[PDB]
Length: 48
Length: 48
Image 1 (tube, rainbow over the protein chains, first blue to last red):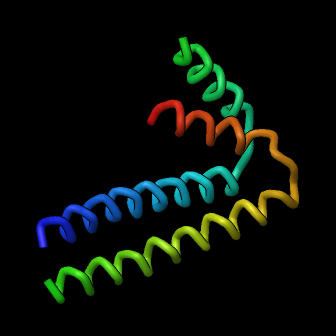
Image 2: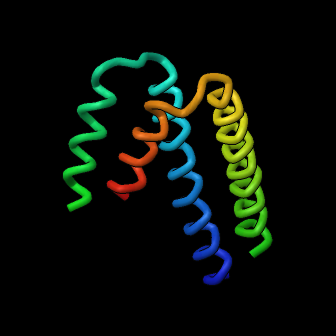
């Protein structure tokens, strides 16, 4: 039961991850502007 | 244990559903080539 619950909790973290991915994908589908370069830059510096 | 396993199986059905949603979204994005959504994905994965 402990093993099954840990597996379920891991699966819930992956589920939530995929939900966030889906939400951000539809948000990115809804509109495209110069913002994409600013968020690219802000993360590209964060690579350092 | 039976209840926990059924909950895990339901969570797996939702996981598979979100995976199918993600796949269909990327398939729809392939209609207009990678340009900003690749950068926004890179932002999310880098932040993770």
